[PDB]
Length: 263
Image (cartoon, rainbow, N blue to C red; front, side):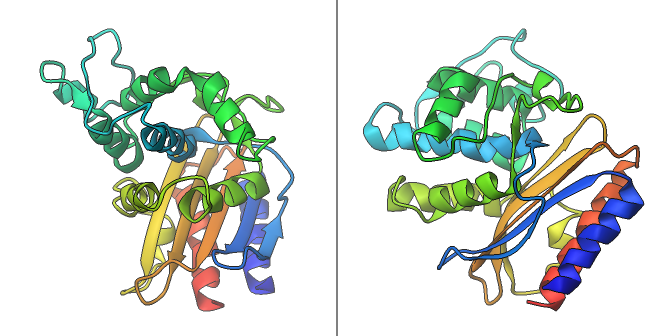
């Protein structure tokens, strides 16, 4: 809705930075709204959905098993590892690692999963071979969050991200069991509190993945819809703002409000 566009323009003016935005019908694939959909934005932790997407693709091929247990060291623990720091002795399964990566945004869990698939270059190769020749991951956690101006490393466009997410959740790439698993992990997201979920009415379905980085980097990707079933995909990014985390959350929150209001 045009009223959602002005909120994005409102967000742009108040934050003093670019705001990437796109709205996409989950079923048909028709873009309902798009603001700067061809510009690049830092992915931040939103890449962790694409990460486990490649992981599930390997699971389908038999190259990976969700029950496989991975042990790791203390030297592997990077900043913000709320789950993986608790399992140095017993280790964690691939399933548990993806759960920590998508629900808790465990940075160490993400790196461990990246090692399984062959690193960021292989995640980029994965996205490339599913028709996404725009999105690229170059670095590991937490270096991928640097968000240097005009740096195209670890970035994406709202359009590429939205269509990629749709193809993972509902596309022909992954099996039915894996599509359900990925959206289940997203539905159980714990660290997207003051965003789209803040404007989400009761009974509405949401499965998302938020992100935060340096230099005012904020973002979220989500499949949601009323009556407990997802019907649209929403992708929103921003970077460059000197604003606090609080306003960046509330700006994206206000964008979600008009989205719901003019559903």
